[PDB]
Length: 257
Ligand SMILES: *[C@@H]1O[C@H](CO)[C@@H](O[C@@H]2O[C@H](CO)[C@@H](O)[C@H](O)[C@H]2NC(C)=O)[C@H](O[C@@H]2O[C@@H](C)[C@@H](O)[C@@H](O)[C@@H]2O)[C@H]1NC(C)=O
Ligand SMILES: *[C@@H]1O[C@H](CO)[C@@H](O[C@@H]2O[C@H](CO)[C@@H](O)[C@H](O)[C@H]2NC(C)=O)[C@H](O[C@@H]2O[C@@H](C)[C@@H](O)[C@@H](O)[C@@H]2O)[C@H]1NC(C)=O
Ligand SMILES: *[C@@H]1O[C@H](CO)[C@@H](O[C@@H]2O[C@H](CO)[C@@H](O)[C@H](O)[C@H]2NC(C)=O)[C@H](O)[C@H]1NC(C)=O
Ligand SMILES: *[C@@H]1O[C@H](CO)[C@@H](O)[C@H](O)[C@H]1NC(C)=O
Image (cartoon, rainbow, N blue to C red; front, side, top):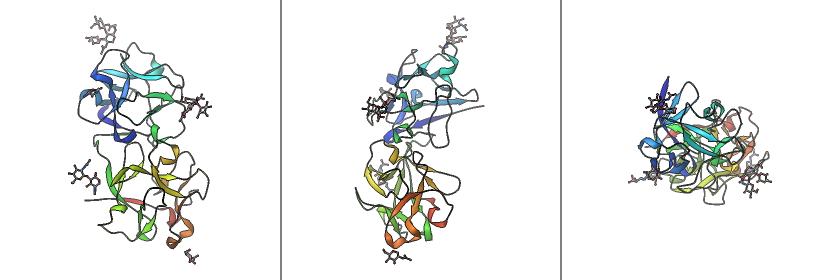
């Protein structure tokens, strides 16, 4: 079967066929999300992703190769097949390379690159082109809360009026301070017990997260998950740690009004 959606990525911008041209070889880029046909992507059971009747195509299968639109019947078969890993990557199976936005700006051209699980490599296939705004409820039914740039995140009693408990879940798989959307939940390293803080969004692997089906919030590069340190909310420390399924690693999003 087939179905059509937008594809939201870095900084909440959308995958867009540049200038709305359908000529073979036209690059894909980031552009602010809308309803224009050059942002509407049809996913077919043959693993093609189509816009304006043509296919998302790797113009080469090397690190740094450009991704373009191209006639689906004349492109190389290997170059038009894509899958959508549950962590939000868009992968070309033949090469193993993944769709990447190398800069945050509008008009950045999308490339196939080595998978480093970067936030620049995160995408969401959806008709809602706005970030989802939610509280993140965890251990002891408390809420995850921001506390400024460079500072730790930590747990507090949930309050409908606390803006610092309000998170924008962006299409690039970043978790952002809703009121200050240039700031990202960031692990301060990839090792167990590294602290989770807020830092300027930079596309990094340390800023990419995945909400899995076991109630964990996973950092794909490290493999490790958000953890209320020592099950002790008074420490005011959230770390990354291996997944245990314990109550201090369970989370659920609660959509905000
Ligand atoms: C695949 O392409 C990437 C983008 O060109 C390479 O990473 C980039 O390497 C640049 C130096 O050549 C570096 O200044 C860029 O910031 C970096 N981009 C990022 C953020 O990944 C990548 O090169 C590998 O990784 C980089 C960071 C260095 O460690 C290089 O020595 C590595 O070769 C390319 N991968 C390969 C396998 O060449
Ligand atoms: C993809 O490239 C194909 C090969 O060049 C195009 O099919 C060819 O379209 C020609 C111009 O319309 C037509 O004279 C040829 O007979 C046909 N060739 C073959 C081998 O089918 C194709 O065009 C689409 O498909 C054809 C069948 C017609 O329906 C066209 O009007 C379609 O545009 C190219 N696809 C696209 C979307 O451009
Ligand atoms: C989250 O932050 C967003 C962005 O600042 C807030 O959305 C703005 O809200 C005002 C008032 O309703 C609107 O007029 C703007 O159009 C909104 N902007 C955007 C870009 O969406 C939002 O209210 C915040 N809180 C929640 C719960 O979503
Ligand atoms: C939790 O952390 C606080 C703050 O550091 C500390 O005073 C308290 O003793 C800890 N509780 C436990 C059970 O370790």
